Amino acid sequence: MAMDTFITRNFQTTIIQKAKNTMAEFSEDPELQPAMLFNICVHLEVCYVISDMNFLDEEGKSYTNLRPQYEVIEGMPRTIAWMVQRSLAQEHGIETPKYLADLFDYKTKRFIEVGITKGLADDYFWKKKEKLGNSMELMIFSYNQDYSLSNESSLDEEGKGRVLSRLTELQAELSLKNLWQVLIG
Ligand SMILES: O=C1c2c(O)c(=O)ccn2N([C@@H]2c3ccccc3SCc3c2ccc(F)c3F)[C@@H]2COCCN12
Ligand SMILES: [Mn+2]
Ligand SMILES: [Mn+2]
């Protein structure tokens, strides 16, 4: 039971193809980098869990007529993603961040960096913060039901819970299949 089989059984094809495309863009081979493949898949999966469950009307009121609260920037070629990020910044009268974000939040008009860690969410928050400063909001999640967020009006309680349930579900299935070892190494 190898990582490639695991990925096929546990991720949607849209997620898998975007992850593999990203790896190919950076000249990395999914067959030779199975930990990396899983990590990219789960990160993109989280971006979509967040984007697929959060909506706005014209007033800007939240629901779980409607438009998505978030646009996913991750999982497209960087040539395209830079156009998207600059376009969204300029459209909303905000600075274009110098780093390529993961999401754009139409509610708050902020870019978001998503981080997944097998360590302490806090620690990873502060690493990304040291680099990104005030340029973007941060959403950091761990496998052990921890998280660290940079602002009040970002993800709600149910959204936090759904991200964390999914990560916990994936870790459980990896451990069941003796593949969690692969990520630790
Ligand atoms: O955008 C990302 C990125 C993130 O957004 C992130 O949260 C963590 C890590 N990232 N990196 C991802 C990535 C994304 C998700 C999970 C693990 C990895 S591991 C390094 C790596 C990435 C992509 C291709 C590749 F060949 C890599 F080696 C690169 C960092 O340089 C900018 C693009 N990018
Ligand atoms: Mn990214
Ligand atoms: Mn990220």
Image (spheres, rainbow, N blue to C red):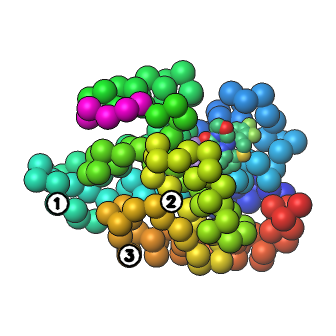
The residue under label 1 is: 61
Is disc 2 in contact with disc 1, using a CB cutoff of under 8 Å?
Answer: no
The residue under label 3 is: 157
User: For residue 27, which quarter of the picture?
Assistant: top right
**Which label's residue is closer to the chain start, 2 or 1?**
1
Q: Quick check: 46 above or below 178?
A: above
Specify whether residue 66 is painted magenta: no
**Which label's residue is closer to the chain start, 2 or 3?**
2
| Mark carried by residue 23 | none
Identify which amino acid the numbered label 1 is placed on. Lys
Image spot of residue 124 (x, y percent): 66, 61
Stretch of the chain drawn in magenta: 92-96
Q: Residue at x 46, y 34 (%)?
A: 97
**SS of the residue at dot 2?**
strand
**Which label's residue is closer to the chain start, 1 or 3?**
1
Q: Quadrant of the C terminus?
A: bottom right
Can you see residue 151? yes
Circle 1 residues within 10 Å: few <14, some 14–19, many ≥20: few
User: For residue 160, which quarter of the picture?
Assistant: bottom left
User: For residue 165, which quarter of the picture?
Assistant: bottom right
Whole-number angstrom distance, CA of label 2 to CA of label 1: 21 Å
Disc nearest the viewer among 2 and 3: 2
In the image shown, does 127 or 161 lie closer to the viewer?
127
The residue under label 2 is: 139
